[PDB]
Length: 95
RNA sequence: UGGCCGGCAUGGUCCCAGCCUCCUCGCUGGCGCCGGCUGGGCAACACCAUUGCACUCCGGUGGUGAAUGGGAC
Ligand SMILES: [Sr+2]
Ligand SMILES: [Sr+2]
Image 1 (cartoon, rainbow, N blue to C red):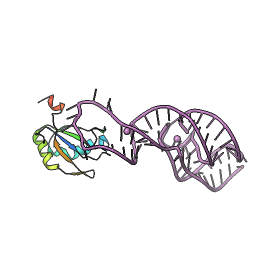
Image 2 (image 1 turned 45 degrees about the vertical axis):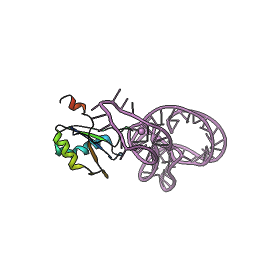
Image 3 (image 1 turned 180 degrees about the vertical axis):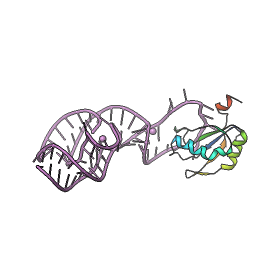
Image 4 (image 1 turned 120 degrees about the vertical axis):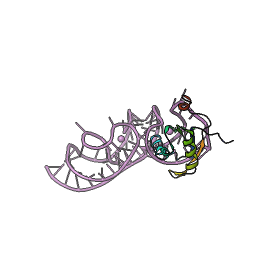
């Protein structure tokens, strides 16, 4: 079952050999044009590696980012993008 | 040598260059042969496993089973 629109996009299929700090930097480099980004969360743990959460301030940004960068070759791999199942805390602490 | 021991070999002190390494990366570390014991840590690196929905840092295993020469006294 797909997912409903969200402030946060969930990206996976990312190159696992990239360190956390660099991955966050590179992700911002390509995703900041879609709108203000509140934060990017990345973890290299067994369960969370290869994935990232880009948290946009406005849902239109996420939606854009989602449609525009679906399948984008990043670090030699096609980026897969979806909306996050639930709202990230940063967003809850507001709306 | 990450810590520890044994056997054998080996004149010494330096100077220059090169080379080596998971555990004080370098000029007041190290760079003969052989065998056995043991500690730490995944931080870097590699390999294996993982396609995974978080907002709690947190998979496993491996490496030293390493590295040459010149010169001055
Ligand atoms: Sr050493
Ligand atoms: Sr590890």
